[PDB]
Each structure stands twice: as C-alpha cells, then as structure tokens.
Image (cartoon, rainbow over all chains, first blue to last red; front, side, top):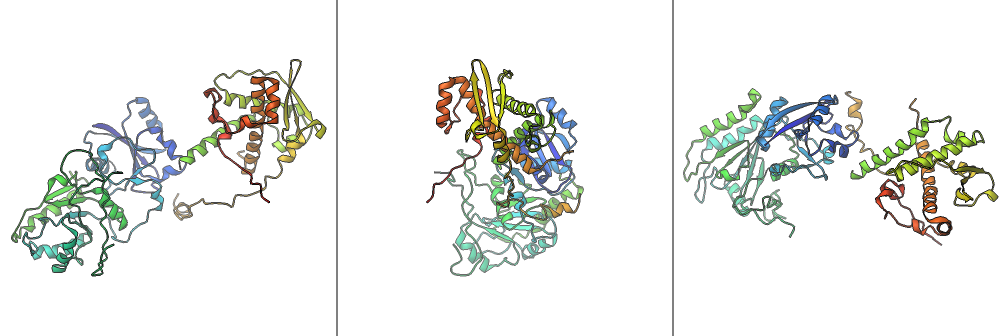
Length: 307
Length: 210
C-alpha cells in the first residue's frame, strides 16, 4: 500500500505504453532519445520531498500524484485510466536492470523494452476491443456425454458478439484430444476467435506437432507457465501472461477490458469481471441475465469510469 | 544497450577534458597551433595542462600537483627516438621532459576515413519520416577523433612518468626496455581510479602472416 506518481510524456511519439520505475535516476539507463518511446511512467511516491520538488520544477513532461493503497494490477489501471481520461492503454515495459520489487504485479505481461519499436500493428479489429475468456469444463456445455448449447439463442449470441468488436478466447482446461470431436459435433470455428487447451494443471516450471489426421491449423499449447508462486497450495489460475502472449502473437496489442467466465472463482486473479457459470446438466436457457451482466460490464466505461 | 550508457559516460569524460582546454588560452585548431614555432611555450603549456588533467582524473583523491618542471622541444631524429615522442628526464634535481613536435604533427594527418561499416539507424518512417511529419558550436567528428587520439597518445607518457617517479630511474629504463608491466593490468589500489583509464575500453592485436 503506497502513494504513487506518474509521468505523462508531452509528445506521445509512441503512444499507449507505460513503464514502471525503481529509481528516478533510472532515467540514465534510458539515456538520450529513448524517453520519447513511452507515454506514461509510474513510480512509487518520493520518500524525500526534494525528489518530488525537483519533479515539480521539471517542465519536460506532465505528471500526476495519487494514493493507491489498492496494490492491484486492474485497480491501478483503473486509477490511471481515470487520471488520464483514456479507455485503452499499452503494455508495461521492463529492462535487464530489474524492475522494483513490486512483485505483487508478478502475474502480467512484461515487455522487453527494445521490442517496442519492433512492434507491429494489427488488422484484426478496426477499433479497440473488449475480450472475454471461457472454459469448457462445466462451462456452457450441458454436462452429459453429448452436449447441447444451453440455448441456441446463446449459440447465435456468440456470433452477434462480433457486432460489438469484442474478442472470444476459449481455454479448455479439459483434455486436448476430445475438443476436436466436440467442435465436429457442434462447430463454432465460424463463431469463435481463439482456442487453447490443457490448462488444467500448474506444473514444475523451473530450471531443474499436431493436426496429423485432419488438417487443423492449431498449435502446441506449450507448457510455458511458471510455477509463479513457490508455495503449498492448489490453484491453476488463468494466466494473463499467457493470454496476452497469444494475443500479441495474433498481433492483438491493445484492449479496453477483459472478462472471465468460469466455474472457479479461485483462478480469477483480479480479472476485470467474473461470471461464475451455473452448472447445468440440462438446458437452463437462463442466458438473458448473463447477456445483461456482460452488456453492463461493457457499458461501465461509457461513463468514462468503470466504478 | 547496457553498452550505450558506458559509451555515453566515456564521451562525457572526453568532452569534460576537451572543453576546459578548448576554451582556456585556445587560439587556433591543434594543427594550426602545432604547425609552427608560434609560442612553442604555448604548446608546452598545453601539454603540461593535459598532463595535469591526466593526473587529476587518475589521482583525484588529492588534487594537488607539483607545478614545477621543464619543457624541451626538438626537431631531429638525433633528438628523438622511435616509439616515445615524449621522454622524461631528471638532471641533478632538474625534472624535465622533451618532445619532438614533427613526429606528432605527421601523426595527426591520416584521420581521413569514414565509418560506412556496421548496423545503425533501424531505418524506419517511425525512426525518421514520422517526425518529418508532426513536430559558435562548430565541432566535427574528425576533430574529436584527432583530440581523443592525442589524449590516448599522452596516456602512455603519463603512465611511464608515474612509474618512473614511484620506482626510480632503474625501473624507468627497465620498463622502457619492456612495458610488460603495462601488459593486462587493471589490478591496482583504488586510488588509481583504474576504470578512469582508457586502457580499459578497447583492445587490439596483430597477426603475423606469411
């Protein structure tokens, strides 16, 4: 729980992006001209008032000051988007000069700064999208061996979601092999954007080919997720790290918000919204309230603050 | 790059050296000054001041320096030896140094190359044409090269002098016959500020072939 401060660059010669500082003097690692590549830069609030005073004397950029005891990724993003009246923001940069130990921010994408100039821009949407994450396990299937959609209304609602310019990401924790048969039974390849599998487990991520039968164009959902917590518990969170990774692999580079729809609250690590799926061995046809929830969650920022 | 700020620090120390003597008593470009006898004493004082700065940055822990020593300019091979255009001497208390100007003058003449060599730029509209849209100081790289060259030239001399002072004439001769002590030694007491010294920066070798 700390006070916090942020740079706002005068000329966003590169836009949307933000950086995080351990020292005000870290600027020396950045040196000449490199500063023009970042729109904002957060720093933990000065302990010495002279630092803040020198900041106040500096004219090279605008700045803001605030309290954020809420040491959370999404809450900090909310506060910054409030301060700078902006719906969408870029990635958070990092250097070999290791970041400050604000390691509660551990679970996120980390941008090796030099890539920033190398970054592409993407066709995939003409406007900045929202994103929604889904599962197979007990999720929107009926629970029997052969599954209906909980409503064909939902079936077509998935398609219409494209009208809003929002992204559909399914990561089955369930086993890889059966999902192909599942989609052959009911195909949403024309209805859904992104597919991932085998997330069920956390595994010892420490230092110590597919589509042979039918020409699917899928991939090894490679196990590249850290143990990340080095502790005795039982949790397999959905990983914003991996999600943003595959997004930028699809050149998806900016977004307004991300929501999770899942049967496990535990896996939600401060996702913007969570929809606990109702378990359903029969077609509940309840979707309209899910629709309402999602629509209002989207609408939150039409007032220019999520609340 | 992590290399980048080290390069910037090196450039910074360079310019920090340069400007002070580029303003104090600075009449004309180095070549113009050295071309002729014109104030041989000015050339002497310039070299002395350079040595003073070198002693400063090598041993800044104590800034004081004995200002008193003698200068000799000479013009003939009889008056000079290859490889050491600067030579320190001591005569019955008379600490003196000697230099052949023409050697160094000839030296500071071939710096005519250009660096069409390796990667830079990252040529991009974003790199350039993006800011083509939207939004007496006279110095040049060749002169900076010349001056850095002369500085590195004086480095050898200064190290020779320091050792001669600290170890006496015998080791002065010994080192002149064999600079192996120079061979691969950052190791020092911190008072040398050995990282300040430009031997640490870049490396060279010959291959004997055919």
